[PDB]
Image (tube, grey):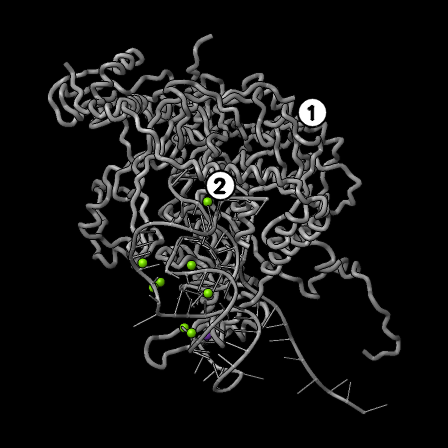
Amino acid sequence: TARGTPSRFLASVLHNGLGRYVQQLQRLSFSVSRDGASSRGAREFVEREVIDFARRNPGVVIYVNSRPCCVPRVVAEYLNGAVREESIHCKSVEEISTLVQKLADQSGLDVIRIRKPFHTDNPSIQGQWHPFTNKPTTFRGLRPREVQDP
Amino acid sequence: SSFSRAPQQWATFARIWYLLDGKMQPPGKLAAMASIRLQGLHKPVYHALSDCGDHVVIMNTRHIAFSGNKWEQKVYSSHTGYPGGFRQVTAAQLHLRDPVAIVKLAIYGMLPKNLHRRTMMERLHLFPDEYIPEDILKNLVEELPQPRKIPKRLDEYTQEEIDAFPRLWTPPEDYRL
Amino acid sequence: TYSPLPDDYNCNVELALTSDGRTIVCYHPSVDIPYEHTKPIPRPDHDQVLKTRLEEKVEHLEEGPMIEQLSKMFFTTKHRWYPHGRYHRCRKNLNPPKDR
Amino acid sequence: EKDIIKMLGLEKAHTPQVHKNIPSVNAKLKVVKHLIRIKPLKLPQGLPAEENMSNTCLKSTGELVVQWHLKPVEQ
Amino acid sequence: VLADLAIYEPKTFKSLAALASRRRHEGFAAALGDGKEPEGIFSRVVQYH
Amino acid sequence: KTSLSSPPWPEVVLPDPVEETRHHAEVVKKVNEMIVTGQYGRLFAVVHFASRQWKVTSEDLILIGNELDLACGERIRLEKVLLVGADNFTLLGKPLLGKDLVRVEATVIEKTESWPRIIMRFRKRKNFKKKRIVTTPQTVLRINSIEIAPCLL
Amino acid sequence: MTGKELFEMWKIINPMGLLVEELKKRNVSAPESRLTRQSGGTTALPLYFVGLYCDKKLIAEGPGETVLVAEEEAARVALRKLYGFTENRRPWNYSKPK
Amino acid sequence: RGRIPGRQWIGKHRRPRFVSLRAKQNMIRRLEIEAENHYWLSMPYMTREQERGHAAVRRREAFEAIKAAATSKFPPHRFIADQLDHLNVTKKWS
RNA sequence: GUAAAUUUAACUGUUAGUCCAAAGAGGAACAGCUCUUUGGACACUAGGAAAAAACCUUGUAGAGAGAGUAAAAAAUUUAACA
Ligand SMILES: [K+]
Ligand SMILES: [Mg+2]
Ligand SMILES: [Mg+2]
Ligand SMILES: [Mg+2]
Ligand SMILES: [Mg+2]
Ligand SMILES: [Mg+2]
Ligand SMILES: [Mg+2]
Ligand SMILES: [Mg+2]
Ligand SMILES: [Mg+2]
C-alpha cells in the first residue's frame, strides 16, 4: 500500500533534458551460463542482440561474464549511484531485450510512489495567492471601527 | 511575487480577523458566514489538513432577530446526565440567560463534526453589545457585510421618499378615521 | 463605464476579442497600493548608577497553567500541547520528501 | 425487454445505433420505447460514398456529415 | 486547472471570472430582448466543420 | 417603488457593440505590441495531453500515464494549448489557440513504469478473494520552452 | 540556478543598506517604508506588508511576521526587481544558438 | 421517539416517502423523451407488404456463415518442428 | 432484427427462499402472516432513499490528481357577523 511504502516527488537527475539529455544508464553486467538450461535465452541475447545494443548505446559499458550460474542476472548501474539487479532466469531473447531496453530508458530513481504527476520550481508567475490578494485598500489604511485623529 | 521562501509561505497561511455586526440579523445567516471563515472555506488554498482557519468576531449578538415566531417556538434542549435532568428552554429564555448562546450554538452546529471543530470555536469571538476589547479591535482586518438588509421604520423615511410614493385612494371627507 | 468586476483590488481586467473571434485576449496589469492608503511604520518604541543587567523573567510554570497559556496565545485547544508516547514519535518520518 | 435490447445491438448505453424505419423494426422499438431515444437520421450531403467513407461523423443533431475537417468555418 | 489558476495565477483567474461575469450578463440581455438584436460579442460561438 | 417593485440586482447596461468593437481592437493591438517588444517574462501554458489538461511552464516536469512511442531525448511539440498567460496579459482559446500563436515544446527524458499497484477483491462469507499487481507504463516529459508570436490581429 | 532565488545563492547582510546605495547611483530618492497591510498585530501570529515608496511611488512590497522582518523582505524584493532577478523573469534560453 | 414499526420500506406500516421538486422534473424529462419516440414511430418508410423479403438474401447468407463456422471445428495441425524444437532446452555454448 | 438452437457423448451440484409490484385464496379487505400465478430484485458490482439483502439508478471488471450524466432534498396552517 502507499502508507506501508516510501514515497517521493517527481524529479530528474541534474535537471536532465533541460540543457541536454544524458543517458542515466551507465553500466550493464550480464552473468550467463555456458551450460545452464535457464540461461538459454541469455546466451541467445549475447550471440546476436548485445552487439547491436552496444552500438546504439555508446555511453553504456556492458560487461558479459560467462560463469556457471543457476539464475542468470543483469545488473544496471546509473549515474546517480543507484544499482538495480534484474533476473533473466528462463526468459526468451525478446523478453530480455525488452527488459534491457527498459533499463536504458529509466532515470535510475527509486521506483516507488510519486506524490504528484508533475514538478515545477516556479509554480506561480503572477504571484502566489495570499489573503490580501483580492482585498481592496482603504484610505489611510484604517481598520474597521477605527477612529482617526482622536 | 519574488518573495523569499519563508515569508511567502507565512503570507499565504496567515490568519485574518473578520468583524461581523449581528444587529437585527438572523443568527443562522451570521452562522453561515462565520462557519465558512472559521473552516477556511473562503480561501483558494483551503484544505482540511492545512489548518487555514480565520478569526471571526461577531458583535451585537444580543440584538439578533429571529424570523417568524422562533423566539417562542425554537427550543434548545440539553441533558445534564443525572436522572430527571432533561432541560428544554425556548430561544427567548436562552437569549435572556445568555446573550451569546444562540449565535454560538448556531455556529457550532454548522462546523464539521470532527476534532477540528473545537479548535475552530477558539477562533470565534462573540460579544453581546458594541463593546469589543482593544486587543481584539487592534487586529481586525475586514468587516463583513450584514447578510440581511434591515428595513427602515415608517418614521425613518425622508419627506422626499414619502412624497415620492403616490397616494393610492381618496378617503371620504366625512369619515371619522 | 461598464466593467464586469471592480478594478480596485487585484488588477485592471480588460477583455477583448481578435478580428476572427477565435481568441480571447485579457490584459490585466497589476494595481499598486496608493501612498494615501498606507500607514507609517511605528519606528518609535534617571541617573542610574548600577549597570543594567539582563533579568530572567521566565518563571517556570506547571504543565497545567503552561498549556492554558499556550492555548490562549495561539487560540487552540489544550489537547495539542500534551505529549505523545514513543510509539507515535518513532513513526514520524524525520526525513520527509521535499518538493521544490 | 432485455432480449430485445440485445437484438437491436443496444447493449452499451449512450452508443448510437442505426436501424431501418420499417414496421418490423418499429415493432421491436415499441416494446422498449421507454428505454431508448429515437431520432431520425439526417443526410445533409447525402449518403457517404466510397471516397469519403473514412471522413464521416455523426453529430449530436442526428446529422451524418460526410466531411470532417476539424477546422473552424471561414464564414 | 481552474483550481491551480485560482492559487497561483490570481490575475488570470480574475480575468476568467470577469469573462464569465460578462457572458452571464449577455445571457440576461438576450433573455430580456425580443431577439431583434445581434448576439453578444462574447456570446458568439465558433463553429467547427 | 416598493421592495418587490424592482429586481434586487442592479441594472446592467452593456457597452455599445459598435464602440466596443473599436475598443477590443485597441486592446488586442496593445497586447500584440507587447509581444513584438518582448514585454513578458516567464510564460505558463495549459496544454491538453493524454486526456488531461496540464498547467505547465518552462523547466517543468509532467508524468504521463502511458507510453508515447518516443525515444528518450526526442523533442516534441504540444499542439493543444488552451491557455497561455504572462505577468500582464493572457490569451484564451475557443477552445484551442492557433499553432502560429503559441508553440510549446517538450523533451522525453525518462520512460519507466509505475510502482506496483495492488488490486484486491474480497467478499465476506463467500470464499471470494483474488489479487492482481499491475505496473502502468509512464513517460516523463520536460517542458523546455514556451514561445508566443505576434499573431493577434 | 533553476529554482534557486537570487539571495539564496548570493547571501547578503543588511539588504536595505545596499538598496539605498543602488538608488543613489540611479538618482532616485531614498525609499520610505509604510505598512500597506496588517493582520493580527496584537496576536502571536502577525502579518505585515511593508511597502517601499520612492517619490510616493511603490517600488516593492514584502510580507513578514514583524515590521522589521517585513521591511527587510521588501528591500530584498526591491533589489530583485532592480537587478532583474524576479521570480517571473524570462527563463534561460537553452536552445541551440542561431 | 418516532420509530417505524418493523422495517422502514416494507410492511403494512411504512415510512412515508415524498416526491421532491427534482424528482418530478426527472420524470417529466423522461416523459418528454418518450413522447418524441411516439412521433418517430408513427411514420414508417415502407408498409409491411413492401418490407417483405427485402433482406432475405442477406439473412440467409449470414446464417450460412454461422453454419460454416460451426461445422469447421477440428483439431489443429501438428508439426514436426514444434516437437523437435523442444530439444533446444539443452542447447549449450561450445 | 438478430445468433443462437436442437441433437449426440460424459457428469456434478441445486431440489429447506426472501421482499417488492400485479391477479387471487386462507386469516381479521391483521402481520416482517400463509399458499399459488406473472414479473422484478436479492443470495455479484456501484450510486441514491439517513443507517439499510428485496424500493430507485446502474451492470463486464485495469491505470489517470480529466469530462458529461443517471437516480437523487416535503409540502401544508384553517371557523366574527345582521
Ligand atoms: K414496516
Ligand atoms: Mg467540545
Ligand atoms: Mg426496525
Ligand atoms: Mg446425474
Ligand atoms: Mg413471508
Ligand atoms: Mg420469482
Ligand atoms: Mg442458499
Ligand atoms: Mg450508503
Ligand atoms: Mg464500464
Quarter of the picture for ligand 4? bottom left
Residue A126 image position (x, y, % from top left): 49, 31
Examine the image and state in which quarter residue A41 appears: top left
User: Is D37 on the left-hand or right-hand side of B83?
Assistant: right
**10 Å neighbourhood of mark 2: few (<14), some, or many (≥20)?**
some
Q: Is residue D20 shown to the viewer in this render?
A: yes
Residue I10 image position (x, y, % from top left): 30, 51
Q: Residue furthest top?
A: G98
> What residue is shown with label 1?
D74
User: What chain letter is assigned to the residue under label 1?
Assistant: D
Q: Is residue C36 shown to the viewer in this render?
A: no
Q: Is residue B176 above or below residue B124?
A: below
> What residue is shown with label 2?
A132
Examine the image and state in which quarter residue C23 appears: top right
Q: Which marked residue is nearer to the observer: mark 2 or mark 1?
A: 1
Q: How many marks?
A: 2
SS of the residue under disc 1: loop
Mark 2 residue type: Phe
